């Protein structure tokens, strides 16, 4: 009475059965292979906000390499960040950028965990480098946490952030 | 007489044909896209064993970021490692850890080759950094090889290992 | 009159319907999972050519870790590179290598953008490190651009290039 059907990502049109493919994730060249969508390298300014250990903000020059469903951030501060404590929480919210924002949004899978972030900066003429960690707290906002290299009030500069997300 | 059938990863149930999907590798949102499984960041201690150029062992504080089927290791020694030669082979066996061990096991594809490992440590107050290489020698055990920065007996400290595996 | 058919990467043979799979990209273990093809670590010499800011060339010792459809380059110069300007364009053409060249060729998706490249070198005894960028200009040729750390004629040495491509 009832025959045979196909559930997504399989679909049918005029009795032709197909694989629906996310071009950012895969594609066919006779077989199923990796993504066919253009990579892009976006460059923009992102104003990060201290949210604990600081109420200052900081301009970061960002390069985002969106390639397949991997997106890698390479960022640089301009100007200084005022820090109050010895650890600082620094927040990146998509609003504060100045564009398919899509491929700057982590998949729900990725958001489940804290992720590695490479951080360095200068504090009164000494360089500091730390293995730090980021966490998304909503799909549009993540926060990195790293030590500031001392106590009480100071101004760090030449802040670099290297990280990546699965979108 | 004989009709039409479907081979894995295609399967059928009540005449509904499906793509069986590894959630750590892909998933559907109408189309075939990347993984839907939660990422996790595990933190644990791994005791590495010198196996040549040393018979000492060394506590490493490990963070493993298991995200999709990529797993990235960021590790730090505590205490010192006694080295005898000028290259050392350092072994990471899953037993020596203190948990889905699954996503700390490389795919058979990955094991076929030696893989890049970032290493640095301090030796009598000088820092040393090397591009080193790891090789799995069984699915549960890999060995990194790196130079020790001198000869005969010494103690290196602040050992860091940054690497990653395809699981 | 006309029934039902299957378009690639779906195919059929003796009324058995299949997923055609790129083994460098995926495979089945009951479900669709990631690649099954061996990783390999190739080691060879690549002669890069200055193409602007220099007409010199430079031997690089290359290690390429081809794993799945990701290929990561770790390279080192031997000898010195003569630089004339304050930025230099350095070109890597597959001809100049001395082997499935296949997995050293970026997918068309990847070529669409400039990509991040890590570079450092020494210039009259000071170390220099820069976040640089590469661009393929044909599927067999890419060019990195980085600053040389000064002006007019000099010789840089101990040049390292760390980058990666989606193949």
Image: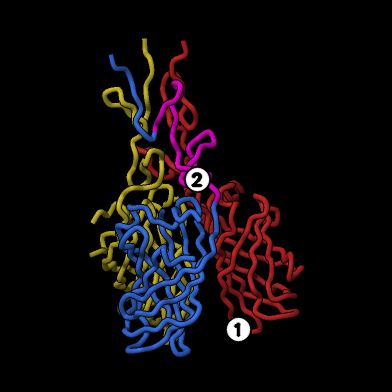
Chain colours: A red, B blue, C yellow
Q: Is residue A24 magenta?
A: no
Q: Is residue B54 left or right of residue B162?
A: left
Return the residue nearer the eye: C22 or B135. Answer: B135
Residue A67 position within the rendered picture, expressed as x and y whole percent measured from the top left: 48, 51
Q: Badge 2: how crowded within 10 Å, few (<14), some, or many (20+)?
A: many
Residue at x-position 46% and y-position 84%: B122
What label sits on residue A126 in the rendered view?
Answer: 1
* Label placed on residue B35: 2
Q: Residue at x 51, y 71 (%)?
A: B61
Residue B112 higher or lower than C109, as above or below = below
| Residue span colored magenta | B10-38
User: How packed is label 1: few (under 14 Cα within 10 Å), some, or many (20 or more)?
Assistant: few
Residue A60 at x, y = what percent? Answer: 64, 65
CA distance separating discs 1 and 2: 42 Å
Q: Are marks 1 and 2 on the same chain?
A: no
Examine the rendered structure and indicate whether residue C166 appears above or below residue A58.
above
* In magenta stretch: residue B22: yes
The answer to which image quadrant residue C163 occupies is bottom left
Q: Could you say whether the residue bearing mark 1 is in a helix, strand or loop?
A: strand
* Secondary structure beneath label 2: loop
Q: Nearer the viewer, mark 1 or mark 2?
A: 2
């Amino acid at each position: 009475s009832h025959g045979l059907s196909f559930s997504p990502p399989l679909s049918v049109a005029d009795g032709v059965v197909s694989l629906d493919m996310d071009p950012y994730f895969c594609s066919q060249r006779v077989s199923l292979t990796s993504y066919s969508a253009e990579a892009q390298l976006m460059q923009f300014r992102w104003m990060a906000r201290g949210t604990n250990g600081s109420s200052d903000t900081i301009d970061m020059t960002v390069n985002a390499h969106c390639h397949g469903r991997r997106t890698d951030y390479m960022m640089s501060s301009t100007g200084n960040l005022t820090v109050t404590s010895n650890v600082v929480l620094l927040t990146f919210d998509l609003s504060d950028i100045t564009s398919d924002l899509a491929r700057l949004v982590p998949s729900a899978g990725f958001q489940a965990a804290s992720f590695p972030v490479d951080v360095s900066f200068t504090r009164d003429s000494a360089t500091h480098a730390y293995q730090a960690y980021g966490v998304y707290s909503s799909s549009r906002v993540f926060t990195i946490t790293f030590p500031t290299g001392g106590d009480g009030t100071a101004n760090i500069r030449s802040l670099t952030v290297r990280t990546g997300i699965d979108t």
